[PDB]
Image (cartoon, grey):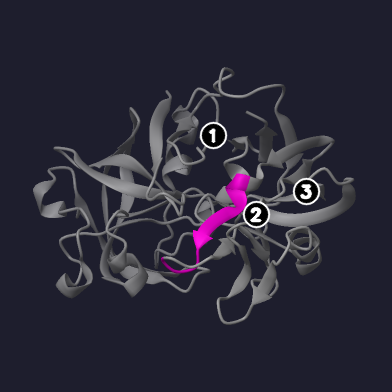
Amino acid sequence: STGSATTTPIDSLDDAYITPVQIGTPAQTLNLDFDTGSSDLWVFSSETTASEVDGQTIYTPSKSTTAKLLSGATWSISYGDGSSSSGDVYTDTVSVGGLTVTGQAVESAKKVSSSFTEDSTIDGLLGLAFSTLNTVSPTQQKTFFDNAKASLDSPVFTADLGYHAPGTYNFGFIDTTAYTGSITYTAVSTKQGFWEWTSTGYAVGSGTFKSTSIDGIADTGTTLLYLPATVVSAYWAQVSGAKSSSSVGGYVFPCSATLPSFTFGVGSARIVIPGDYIDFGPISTGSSSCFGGIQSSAGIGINIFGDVALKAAFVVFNGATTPTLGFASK
C-alpha cells in the first residue's frame, strides 16, 4: 500500500504545516501537524476542556462506530517550545492520503496549553519519530507509520515541504519526479528516539565549506533551524546590523537586509537553503526588526534541522530495519 497527502503552511511565514487526516467511521477530517520529532497522535476532541478550544475541529469518538476506549490508558506530553497536552486514548481507523491503519491509538486531549488553544489552524499532532518516545501509559502505543510499515510497498515516508506553498507527505514510495539529482542517504541513530543524523558541515552564502560534524534531528514539527552558536554567529555576521537580542529571544536583523543562503552537508552532497527561507518577518507588526530563521541550539541540548532546512530538500525517512535519512535537492 501507499498514501499521499498534501501538506499546507498554516500562515504566510510557514510557521507550521497541516495535513488532512481522516479519523473514525464515518470519517472525521482533522488537520494535523505531522511531527517527525515526536511520536504521539493526539487531537482536539469532544473531551477537551471547553475553555481551551478556540476554532479547532474536534474529534468526537462517540460519533465513530469504530472508536474503542483504550481502557486505562492516558498520555501527557511536553514539547521543546514549552507547550503541552494530555488526556485519554481511543483506538480507531486513521487514514492519510488513502493509506488506512486500523486500531491506531488516537490520543484524545482533555487539556491543552495556551499555545495550542491560540492556534486555530492545528487540530492536533501526528507523530512520526520512533515509537519509543510515545507517551501513552501504561501500554506504550505505536505511531501511524509504525503501524502502517509492514503493509507499505517500501517501509518509508517522505517529506517534501514547500516554501510559502503546499507540499507533500508520501508513505510507502519515493516519487522520483519530486527531486533533482540523486538522493544522498546518511546514517541514523535511534538511541534518543529521533531521526538523528550527522551533517558533514556548512557554508554561509558563497563562502567556503567548513567540514565539521553537526549532530542533529530531522524535525518537521520545529519551524526553524537550530545549530551550534559558533555556526549561527558565523551566519549572522554576514548580515549587516544583525544581532542576538535577549529581549526578543534570538537573532534579529534589519528588515532592509538581503540574507545570504546557508548550505548544509549530507555526506558529500550539499543542500542549499536560499536566504529568503531564513526571513521570518517583523518581530511585531510594523517593526523594521525581522526575526531570523537560523537560531542557536545552545540550551536546547540538541541541534534541530527544522522546517527551514527540510523545506529546501526532498527528505526520505527510511524505516527499514536499519533506519536511514535521505536528502535530495529539488
Q: Are marks 2 and 3 in contact (CB under 8 Å)?
A: no
In this rendering, is residue 249 above or below 171?
below
Which contiguous range is marked in magenta? 276-285
Q: What separation in Å lies between label 3 and label 1 (alpha carbons)?
A: 19 Å
Residue 117 part of the magenta segment:
no
170 vs 95, nearest the viewer: 170
Residue 279 part of the magenta segment:
yes
Q: Which residue is mark 1?
A: 158
Pick the quarter of the image with the C terminus: top right
The residue sitting at 77% across, 40% down in the picture is: 266
Q: Which residue is mark 3?
A: 199
**Percent x, y of residue 164:** 47, 41
| Amino acid tagged 2 | Ile
Secondary structure at badge 2 equals strand
User: Residue 141: in sight, yes or no?
Assistant: yes
Secondary structure at badge 1 equals strand
| Amino acid tagged 1 | Thr
**Percent x, y of residue 131:** 51, 53
- Which label belongs to residue 217? 2
Left or right of 162, for residue 118: left
Left or right of 222, for residue 74: left
**Percent x, y of residue 311:** 57, 41
- Return the disc, 2 or 3, that comes first in the chain's sequence: 3
Pick the quarter of the image with the N terminus: top left
91 vs 236, nearest the viewer: 236
| Amino acid tagged 3 | Ser
The residue sitting at 31% across, 40% down in the picture is: 20
Q: Residues within 10 Å of mark 1 (few under 14, many from 20)?
A: many
